[PDB]
Length: 149
Ligand SMILES: Cc1cc(OCCCc2c(C(=O)O)[nH]c3cc(Cl)ccc23)cc(C)c1Cl
Image 1 (cartoon, rainbow, N blue to C red):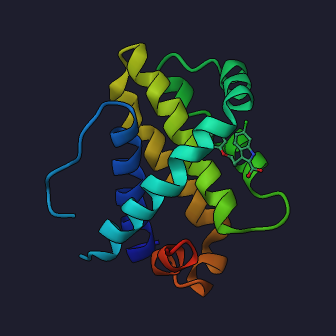
Image 2 (tube, rainbow, N blue to C red):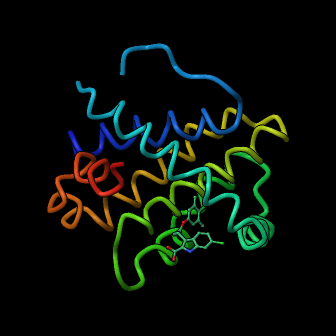
């Protein structure tokens, strides 16, 4: 995906590590288009883990994530849930927020090494399945606008 992929991997990766563990990545992060996306994501996102906790918990249970090898096998189930039907920014937040929910879990069991791979995985599925649509919304820029004020 090049630019779209590089940008999405940064937003999602930082958001997931931010979610499990505190704290920002101080490194400046080819655009402030990314900073604006992280913040929109940070605010619209924290609700979702709240509201869907039971369901999220159930899904994680089925998944059985213990190690890095398990994270590498999640793509098919991840595409399965994501690509059915209608696309919107809200569905994307849900893909990303679960990813953050899964990421928190990864930390608890001291597998924080797995988070980067989880992010790569999520970004692959997002850009592969929804690429054309995303380009149409202008990508991350379209995202911040859709949720603005
Ligand atoms: C990181 C990650 C994200 C995923 O998101 C799939 C699409 C979002 C979604 C949707 C959805 O967009 O229809 N419904 C969900 C329900 C639960 Cl319990 C969890 C996620 C969703 C799905 C999986 C399996 C994984 Cl591992």
